[PDB]
Image (cartoon, coloured by chain):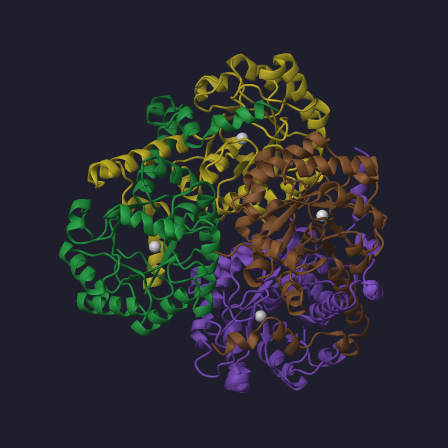
Chain colours: A green, B yellow, C purple, D brown
Amino acid sequence: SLHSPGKAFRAALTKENPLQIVGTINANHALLAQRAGYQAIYLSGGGVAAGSLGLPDLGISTLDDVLTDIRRITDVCSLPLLVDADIGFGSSAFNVARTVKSMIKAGAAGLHIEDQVGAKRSGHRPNKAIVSKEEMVDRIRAAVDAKTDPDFVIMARTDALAVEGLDAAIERAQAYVEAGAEMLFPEAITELAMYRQFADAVQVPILANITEFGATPLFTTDELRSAHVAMALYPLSAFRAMNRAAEHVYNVLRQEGTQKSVIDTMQTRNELYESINYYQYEEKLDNL
Amino acid sequence: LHSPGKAFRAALTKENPLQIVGTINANHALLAQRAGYQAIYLSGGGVAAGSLGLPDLGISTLDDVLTDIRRITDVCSLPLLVDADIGFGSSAFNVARTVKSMIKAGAAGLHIEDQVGAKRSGHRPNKAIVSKEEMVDRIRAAVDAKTDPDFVIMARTDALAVEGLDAAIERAQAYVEAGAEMLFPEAITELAMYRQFADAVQVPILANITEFGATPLFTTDELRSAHVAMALYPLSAFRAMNRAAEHVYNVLRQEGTQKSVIDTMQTRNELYESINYYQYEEKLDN
Amino acid sequence: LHSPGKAFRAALTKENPLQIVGTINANHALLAQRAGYQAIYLSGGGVAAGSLGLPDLGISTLDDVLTDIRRITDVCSLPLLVDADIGFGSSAFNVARTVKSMIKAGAAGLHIEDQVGAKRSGHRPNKAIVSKEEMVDRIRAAVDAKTDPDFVIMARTDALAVEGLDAAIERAQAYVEAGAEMLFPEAITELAMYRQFADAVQVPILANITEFGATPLFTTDELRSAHVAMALYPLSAFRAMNRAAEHVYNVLRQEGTQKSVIDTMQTRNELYESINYYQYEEKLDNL
Amino acid sequence: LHSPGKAFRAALTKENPLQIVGTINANHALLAQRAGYQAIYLSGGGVAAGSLGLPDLGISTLDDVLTDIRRITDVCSLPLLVDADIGFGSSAFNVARTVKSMIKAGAAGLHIEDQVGAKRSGHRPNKAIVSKEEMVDRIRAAVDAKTDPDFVIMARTDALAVEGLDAAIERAQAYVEAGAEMLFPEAITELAMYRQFADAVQVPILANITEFGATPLFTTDELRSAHVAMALYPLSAFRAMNRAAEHVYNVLRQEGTQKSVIDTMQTRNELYESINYYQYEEK
Ligand SMILES: [Mg+2]
Ligand SMILES: [Mg+2]
Ligand SMILES: [Mg+2]
Ligand SMILES: [Mg+2]
């Protein structure tokens, strides 16, 4: 009985409501998130693009850019990792299936696929386009059918709220769940009551994307729990703070000609070592 | 065709000492460029601890490093100096493949060191180094493998803490005589030593101004007085990014919301300007 | 610095038509170079069927191809023309990223086509080819993405098979006008048609002389009489390698030994000579 | 959840000896499966000479191999035994990461040998091996890193040509005592030797029946009589494939057409069947 990341993801859900899931930009941060107490983590598509590739979250990244990051993270962190699979990385059901089987094999616990057209955009940006309900239904069926691990999770995300309104988004969501989606990700919700309506209408775990500087208020876990939200996602929160701190170090070092004045903003060498279990490894080298 | 190595050598000519900052990923390479830096660095200790979440003990593979080189150089035009540890393999063939691959991936140069296979931070105790002759063979293999004459083969010696100053300088002399184009005397404890290395080899020397190690936090002015050609800050940004990320994780877990740390976050517009997001969205919308 | 694209263009002026053979992996690229070829090809059908064991229906990723490009060009100096299908993505950004990545991987040039998704690969006759304007957009994105000016951007279209000769020629002229540097018209069955395309666009024309298809096995002399600039043999060696490998598997399974098929095998020394084995091992012996 | 390693062990109990054929790429792995084989192999010499066009002298990296493992196992369900040379690095940490990475890539098992870093083919002269103690440490690290208990850690010894038979058997016993699950005595020259190894370690032994080497082309019956559990044909198909490819290149270059060699080619219909083409298209 080999370990199933997906099974571990489903177990975390039953032990935390809502289950907080934080984006981890790289393997180091996955370890930091685990040490902080989280029971599940996330690989943001916008993060693979903007962080790993330094590019816009506009469907430019490829499946392999993401797989590389999944392997790096799951090779060292035992937490179940939910992965952003954008639209499935291809225009046919064959692409969706390969995507699903590859991510399962890379170590992921689950993934979400959205109903946007090819060159997708952040769910919190204007002018997004979505495929037909039928089009998305086929994507979902292909994904579910491709599962090699029954516990791997196939989550459906809908970007329809801002484009077709709430009733339309709910109808799509119900059809997606009927097609096999196991959990639902209604993107960029503006009101708490909406989460409740979605939850009541599809009766499968609901995810709330609590990202900064977008269309969604910074709801607390208490508020989300009252709306029956199953999980709270913070996709790029740590990444945003990491970039500001790094930018600060770069600027000060450039203007001052030394980093002395910003040493107090740095994780210490010992802290890094403790994060990666450094001493236990070096000791083994010394014993040779 | 453009030569990153040529751009690196040109940067040395415009700035002395040339500040080179480690960039943990592509995003950070763009931030460094925007900050004014003329050259950047891909830390081996960072590929290990950041990209892999593992100790800087010769566990990473050539490909883990190649992946980060392509990601950074695909989007950032600055010449990238790359940490190639000992060449990734036990033979001269591994060293040669490492050089050719890194050149093709987009790097401007690399540094290879004289430690044994399972190397450790130059700022950690009990390191073990190979003989002067063994290192010379690694250097000769690296130099002869160059497919771009302007690519830089920098030799790093970890011998100061192991055999002493005189021995380390003797090794540096042999390394440069063998073709090493620049020298990286690791974990120097006194400012005066940099001057001695520089005088002894007559090639650009790099000072590794990393935090929490054996080397004082020398300023560019002080390094200039010691004839240092490059001042390297390998993981500085990374260390601050880690503390910031950790703080966000802790606050969110304790408070159930990130409201109280919003003021520590890079804004959406700042991120967008950093990755030229508007240039792309405009094209899509038109 | 060396430019594979420049070498490819040089080969074209020296050999006409230029024979370009598909090489399924690095080893075969070396065999092709030793056989005298001046340019080689990375077949999209071969990456799918050979490297992935999958049908040529748009399932392969850019990365799958890039891996093969690096393996081949890291060891073989011949200019490599690469099949880039439709750019590996939904937009001009994907097309641009594909061009830059392949150049960095070591390729000499690539061909991009006009199908919608993999609809043409799937033999759909209707709404399977993008509009002339959409393909022009793909071509412009690719040409503008070139980091090496000598890298080659070739346009491929099999519109003849669905829209007729006239429409195909009209698309080709628009593609070349948009910046396509060479043309790969697919599904041609008559020599005279190659001449018609050559006259219509006035840029090098590629003839796909693959086996078991609609196109006859035209000879280089015949292709020259039709003004064809290059002759492509995409999977020729691959097909022979598969039959030979299948034969070894069957005999070994039926007989319990490979004694009876030893005579069908490349010997150890022939392999060693192909990969310059001895020059390497000697260096290890004299450390 | 499926375990390739468990499948490999099962194949052994169902086929005696188990014929294991090297598959140079995913396509050939499907050909092997369609031909009736129950286990396949990823040759290190093949990854080097075929996928990279380089000598089998420790130049390939762990990732070069991992890429071929994923390509083969993503499409072919047969258990794949993988050549891991010496663990891909100078330390036990490298050996461990190699084991864990190969399991995740989809392999059923791997073999690690007792040669020095820049290793060479077991059928080449002048090989150098590490001490018995050094190999034992590589084996312990490898066994301890197993994330799937059914994944197989096979130890290979190249000591026969260097230290002789008794020394090779002594090393083999130490390797198995260290946790090696199966044994690969390389470049054996006499059938009887296999029996001596089998009697000495009592774990399944693999015979490397590669061509043009130090080992006679023993039949599966001869191998069974010597108590050999597995018969390996590492590059057999690869060798025939290269000669056939070379022929096509030469003829095409000399004749200006491939007409005269069409009969040596797998047909399009045959290729499509081998990769289940029509199975896809109608979906
Ligand atoms: Mg996303
Ligand atoms: Mg380092
Ligand atoms: Mg093709
Ligand atoms: Mg081998």
Left or right: D258 in relation to C63: right
Left or right: D279 in relation to C195: left
B266 vs B175: above or below: below
Left or right: D91 in relation to A66: right
**Observer able to see residue D123:** no
Left or right: B16 in relation to A111: right
The image position of residue D123, as x and y in percent, is: 81, 47
Q: Quadrant of ligand 3?
A: bottom right
Count of number-bearing discs: 0
The image position of residue B116, as x and y in percent, is: 64, 27
**Observer able to see residue B157:** yes
The image position of residue A153, as x and y in percent, is: 36, 57
Rendered image quadrant of residue A262: top left
User: Could you say which is closer to the camera, residue A75 or residue C251?
Assistant: C251
Rendered image quadrant of residue B162: top right
B44 vs A128: above or below: above
The image position of residue B71, as x and y in percent, is: 48, 47
Please give the name of the residue rendered at 55% of the width and 31% of the height, measured from the top-left corner: B57
User: Could you say which is closer to the camera, residue D113 or residue A272?
Assistant: D113
A76 vs D5: above or below: above
